[PDB]
Image (spheres, rainbow, N blue to C red):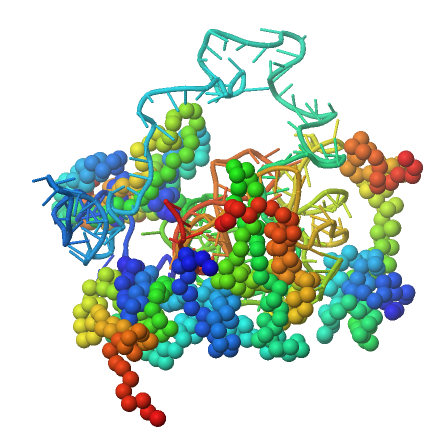
Amino acid sequence: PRKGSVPKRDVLPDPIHNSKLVTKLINKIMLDGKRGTAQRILYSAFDLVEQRSGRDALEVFEAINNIMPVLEVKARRVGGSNYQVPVEVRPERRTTLGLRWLVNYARLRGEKTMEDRLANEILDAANNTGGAVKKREDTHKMAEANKAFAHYRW
Amino acid sequence: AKTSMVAKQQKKQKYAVREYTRCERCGRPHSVYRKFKLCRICFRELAYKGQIPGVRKASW
Amino acid sequence: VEYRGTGRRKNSVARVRLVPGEGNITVNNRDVREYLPFESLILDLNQPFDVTETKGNYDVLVNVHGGGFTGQAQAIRHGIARALLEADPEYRGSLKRAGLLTRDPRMKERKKPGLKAARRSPQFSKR
Amino acid sequence: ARIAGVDIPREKRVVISLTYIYGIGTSTAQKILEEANVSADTRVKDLTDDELGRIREVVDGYKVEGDLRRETNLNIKRLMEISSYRGIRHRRGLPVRGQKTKNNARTRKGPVK
Amino acid sequence: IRIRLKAYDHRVIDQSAEKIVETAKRSGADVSGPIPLPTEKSVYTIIRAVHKYKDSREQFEQRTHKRLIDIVNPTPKTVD
RNA sequence: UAAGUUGGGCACUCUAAGUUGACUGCCGGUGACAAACCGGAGGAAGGUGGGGAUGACGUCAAAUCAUCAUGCCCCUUAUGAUUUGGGCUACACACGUGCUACAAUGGACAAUACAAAGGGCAGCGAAACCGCGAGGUCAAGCAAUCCCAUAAAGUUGUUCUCAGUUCGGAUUGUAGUCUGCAACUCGACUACAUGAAGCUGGAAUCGCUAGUAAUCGUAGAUCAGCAUGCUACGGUGAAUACGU
């Protein structure tokens, strides 16, 4: 509940999910200011996502319940020595960290076309077996499972 | 890069065999003449309309 | 000279780095026809441009700052309009018929405390 | 099948069958078969009925057949014995091209060490 | 003739621009004078051979200072 | 209207080949006894135009007979020297450095539309000779041009398909380039074959701001055998600040 945050001033209206995350993921995986083209590249395999799966793509895009940096170990050298201490993520930071988490930590396993494998890796991703979903348990193993110091906050 | 080629023509440093003597102020280094600092192209333009007694026809 | 252009439209100032000659207008560095949320008149979004007669004679390659959903649109047109004023003095005299300097005499009023929109109020609620 | 008489590799890459066959080291394995729909999904003799026939026609029409290329290569051995090089007096002993007899041992040709 | 005038420095090219107008005035034909030549160059430093702090190659600059004063109708008395 | 424009110095632009306004100085703005510089229309020039350049006297010989002068030194048919038996690279590689292929949110190789810094009387290229390549063209002009332009993105290949597969600019060896005489006992390019380990990584360390750092394009101060490192700016140049 930090009142003081970074000046964001961003917009992301989506008429396919009725929220501000579908366009947030369309602006996170966007390149060379691609907004309208992003939707075309996102709807290019959108039908295949719901065609190569047995669940609803909208709610599948249950695969988003295992890609959040719960408590990542950041850099504060505490007590005059070079040590690492973990920190808590913000609601308006973990959503942007996990949104592009599969667009950088899930580029080692692909097949078929160029946008059909994205949903292929999207399916059966909740169950720890991939690389981008392996960072979720790696985040908690980098701060909680191995006890460390926590007083150095940021 | 004609200005950079008309500048570095007789640069004398550790090796004086690196600078190539060509048209003093004009261009067309090839298809001319170079021995007494006077290229045909430049001399022709420098003798345009009969200037310094140099550009002639024949007359033995 | 057509860079650092001042153009405010309903609280939406935006600088434009237009270059003389090349005409590669790429707002947001890509498509500008499928970016604007609404903007029905996408081709009629530049009214002064027609009189300016420099549609394909300047490359925008700039951005937009602040504004609303459609309030951020039709702001770079005035941004390059002021940039053309410094780029050529003929433009000023060429656009004497229109001459767009200010087009934001009011703001946007919605839900507010005390008064409905701090001006109007409920009157005979229809049953 | 009858590509080499007795298929060495089985149930694997379609171009992996030409890897075990001498004469090609996976450099022209996908540059010899250019027939219509000549794909491969890890199934040499699987999901296929007629495809080797065209591969046996492009391998026979090529300059090198498969045994004649090794025939001339195993016939120039005595043809390169005109007091020149090609291990004239190297293979007989143990020393090989590179003079690695002083740097280490003779890994090329070595009976017992 | 369309020929340039590369002297030494700025005043060296200034005295060569008035001296070429004098020789051209001697001949009986049209003569020019001032010639617009907007300033435009660059500079850079590196190393020399022995020891000489900064600013390698003891020289003035790489300025391409020149001119364009000449004659239009050269006659037999245009040689002087 | 031949990017050697063949014109009309035809009409002037965006223009090159001496600088200029401008920058402190009242400036909109008040310090309280008190200017002002910021920046207001300021001009394109956010204010030394933006800016840089600048090596103040020094300190460490840290470096230098192998950066030389020398307090000066080291060989006197051998440390020279006309130069071969022959050299510091090729063997376990012990590092920094040389790009690299570890992948389908993609490979080598089609035609290919569009600045360059610089290269050149023997040398640059539009379908052509040179479009996998290392090269065997004489050569139009012969250097604002002409050639690289067969460069580049917002506007394109291909194809082999959770991998050894048409993904691997390593070794190795007949052999073509660069040099082949000193490589027999010292380098390489991509190939007729050999084409490794290699699925984001060691001991240990190194790297990140819309015409630029980087990056499609990309560069030498150059030795008769190593260009495979940043190296030039038209445009791909998309992104820019919880905190003192």
Q: Position of residue F19 (x, y in %)?
A: 21, 43
Is residue C56 in sight in this rendering?
no
- The residue nearer to you, when weighing B28 against A136, is A136
Q: Position of residue F203 (x, y in %)?
A: 66, 38
* Quadrant assignment for the C terminus of chain E: top left
Q: Residue at horizontal 88%, vertical 69%?
A: D2
Q: Residue at horizontal 41%, vertical 34%?
A: E46
Residue E57 position (above or below residue F212): above
Q: Quadrant of residue F92?
A: top right
Residue at the far front in the pictured view: C114
Residue at the far right in the pictured view: D112
The number of numbered badges drawn on the structure is 0
Q: Position of residue A102 (x, y in %)?
A: 59, 63
- The residue nearer to you, when weighing F139 against D14, is D14
Q: Quadrant of residue A55?
A: bottom right
- From the viewer's perspective, is F65 left or right of C125? right
